[PDB]
Length: 172
Length: 168
Ligand code: HEM
Ligand code: HEM
Image (tube, rainbow over the protein chains, first blue to last red):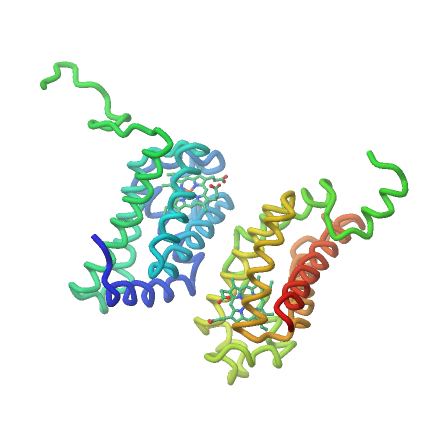
């Protein structure tokens, strides 16, 4: 689903308030994500054993990713008026994560959900249905473009996904 | 290993050697891992010492209290953006056209949209180097100082060339 102009401008304004604290917000997002989904830490050699969120917050590798994530998303959000630019930015991010980092797409789905949870909580006083819908669309946009990029490089998404163990007595 | 005369030129060059690049990249990564706090500290130091530079920022140009400046969303957003753009430069120092493309974009935007006097780039870069020198005072033999001096000169030379290109 495509953002209307009003939806775009709402997201852009809300996002700019987050980006003014780019690292505190990115770190909060990532820590919440890793605490809730420790399997996602597998990709990060320097914090894959960390359990304590206080320790995670101070991990340089985590913090660098937090800063890079916020920068990349900032480029997306500032350019939402330019669909072709949005597509190119997310295609680069997607292809890098598919090919260099080999990240399971499930982690993009999940992280995008965490971002939305953090926004809904940070802006709970200012989050009516119109604004909720705008952010939901942005989540969809991010995941859609990233998965398209994975498909383009030949990642074949499976149902059940690739990580799920086999049923001992399956059914069709 | 180059000839002596080519070494003499590498010393005055714009471009960082592989050894200089790796030094800068390693040290920079420590700063970028604290992108927000470092960027904000850099800008607040800059504006306190160079209040004339505040003029370009419509939402904090009137502020004299450094505590208020520090909390200004416009200042903080710029701090994050500066750190992101510099990070792109440092990570791509091996690729001169990528460095040039990032710094041309920045330079032309600041010349044309923001109408910033180019000297402020020289000044701000200086402040970045001060903050680096403070963070790393032990890991800093003369060659390491020189590597950062070259980065500063590289940034300013690219930006000034972008200003000239757009007819500043
Ligand atoms: C909104 C979603 C995300 C964005 C915008 C994003 C963006 C970035 C960027 C810009 C970089 C640096 C350039 C590069 O090395 O490719 C990066 C690196 C990386 N990303 Fe992401 N990322 C996202 C989600 C994820 C997820 C879900 C994972 C795994 C759970 C992940 C794992 C990694 C890893 C392992 C690196 C390399 C880290 C390192 O070298 O220290 N990313 N990401
Ligand atoms: C390392 C040097 C610098 C870098 C890498 C840098 C980078 C950036 C970037 C990426 C943006 C956002 C995109 C844009 O609007 O152009 C920006 C905006 C801006 N920059 Fe810089 N900048 C630097 C130095 C300066 C200096 C020295 C000044 C003035 C003293 C300045 C004034 C501005 C202004 C006024 C904006 C627009 C801010 C807004 O609309 O909220 N910048 N800069």
